Image (spheres, coloured by chain):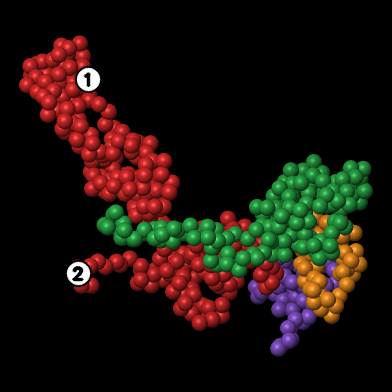
Chain colours: A purple, B green, C orange, D red
Amino acid sequence: VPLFEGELPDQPLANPFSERLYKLRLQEFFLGRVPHIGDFYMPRLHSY
Amino acid sequence: FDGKSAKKKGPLTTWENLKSSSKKVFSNPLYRLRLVAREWGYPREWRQQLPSDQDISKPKTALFEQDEQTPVVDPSHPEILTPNIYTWNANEPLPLESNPLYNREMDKNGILALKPMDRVVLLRALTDWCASHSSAIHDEIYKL
Amino acid sequence: KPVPYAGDIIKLMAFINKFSSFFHSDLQNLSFQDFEVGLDLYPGDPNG
Amino acid sequence: HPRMPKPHVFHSHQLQPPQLKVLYEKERMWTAKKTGYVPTMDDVKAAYGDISDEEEKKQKLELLKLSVNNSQPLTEEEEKMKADWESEGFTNWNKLEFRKFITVSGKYGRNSIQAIARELAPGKTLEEVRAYAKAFWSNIERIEDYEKYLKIIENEEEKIKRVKMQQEALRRKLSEYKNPFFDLKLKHPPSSNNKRTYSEEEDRFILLMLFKYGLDRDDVYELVRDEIRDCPLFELDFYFRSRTPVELARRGNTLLQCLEKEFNAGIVLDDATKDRMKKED
């Protein structure tokens, strides 16, 4: 993680649930997108 | 007292707050809401939906333009800014008695005085105008 | 099961999640089932 | 001693000729001679022209010997021809009736006869308005402060027209693209100076929704909020909700302007040309 400073400030594989920019726009009980079918939703609780 | 108030810290409502002795805590907020609701907009299922399949929002209600002003007394400007105007087909809310908002019980009874689906509708609505008007959070989100 | 009323609940919950500071802790662990039973909703009907 | 060589009121003009004011001064003119009112640096004030000058001994004396020795002491023609000069005007349209008339005409357009008249009925009957409006343009020169009074007319209509070809402009595009909700392009004016919060296809919907209403220039911004309140895919955004139709104007107008600036070479392509009967175009 400390390597990615001059690079992206957050990892391509990072924690979404620490971003104040990706906070409002985020949907989380999404659980999966599947072609020709749709999307899979998992309301589980608060995480903020 | 927007956002910061006398009781600034914490969620605004507590168990004792609901279990308080006011016994009709829902009254004044319900009053305030039935005031602001008519102009704040309604969901379809709480709109007085058109029986008339002619005052669709897309057309208008009635022909306010009795006739087009073809014989302009000013031929120098044959253009007309009043070609054909109508009466307006805004969607209406229900009658107040047909407005479950106007069911007195919630003052004391609380949210459990309705049909379930209607309860759902009102909650979605309360979220709606809270996000649109709870100015504290409303600015906070845009800040964030 | 056809549940005409779920995604509404979903918005309820996600909103509540993003606004944790605004909400009671008892609100913070709420679930879908809480609302189902409490609000008296049963699945199955395409009509509610 | 002093008469009024400032004749009967004309600032609240009723579209009247100035020889009428000449004949109103003719009423002064006998009154000066009959009742012995000598023109004086007080009285001679429309023809004052004497600022510590010796025009006083002559210009005032000109009006003096003219008024006292009046060779038109309300000759019978003066009563008659003044009456026609005040008849040819429009007595009703005083500045009250005047200003409303001209303001409401400028509002709904220089030609919205019935529209402004349905409000102007207390002003007077419609054909009087038709007559009065007619001679109004012909005798706008007979109107004081008339150019600005015309500016409040023609400029007023322009913003109204501005939507008219914007009505036209959006007619184009929503008729132009094939699946604009998946085909549209406005990268000609991408953005002026913005935190560019609303992504395109969001806005494609809204403009689809705005124009499927069309450029109603009345209430659409109220209406689409309701759709955003109600759109199953668009209920999913919350930023779409904390934006009331008031702010939705800010965005909506902007994109109106965006398509406007995109089509600024294409709106006027079918906007501002009207032909007439006797010139090939």
Kindly identify which residue carries mark 1. D4
Tell which subunit mark 2 falls on. D
Q: CA distance from mark 2 to mark 1?
A: 54 Å
User: Is D40 situated left or right of D233 in this image?
Assistant: left
Which of the pair D173/D28 is nearer the observer? D28
Name the residue type under label 2: Lys
**From what the image shows, is residue A34 above or below residue C41?**
below
Residue D116 x, y percent position in the rendering: 40, 49
Residue D43 x, y percent position in the rendering: 19, 18
- Does residue D19 appear anywhere in the picture? yes
Question: Badge 2 local density, few (<14 within 10 Å), some, or many (20+)?
Answer: few
Which of the pair B16/A20 is nearer the observer? B16
Which of the pair D216/D194 is nearer the observer? D216
- Does residue D198 appear anywhere in the picture? no
Q: Secondary structure at mark 1?
A: loop
Residue A45 x, y percent position in the rendering: 85, 68
Name the residue type under label 1: Met
**From what the image shows, is residue B6 above or below residue D106?**
above
User: Is D110 situated left or right of D223 in this image?
Assistant: left
Residue B86 x, y percent position in the rendering: 49, 59
Which of the pair D215/C26 is nearer the observer? D215
Q: Tell how many labels.
A: 2
Quadrant in the picture for the C terminus of chain A: bottom right
Check residue D279 in the rendering and tell me which mark sits there, or answer none. Answer: 2
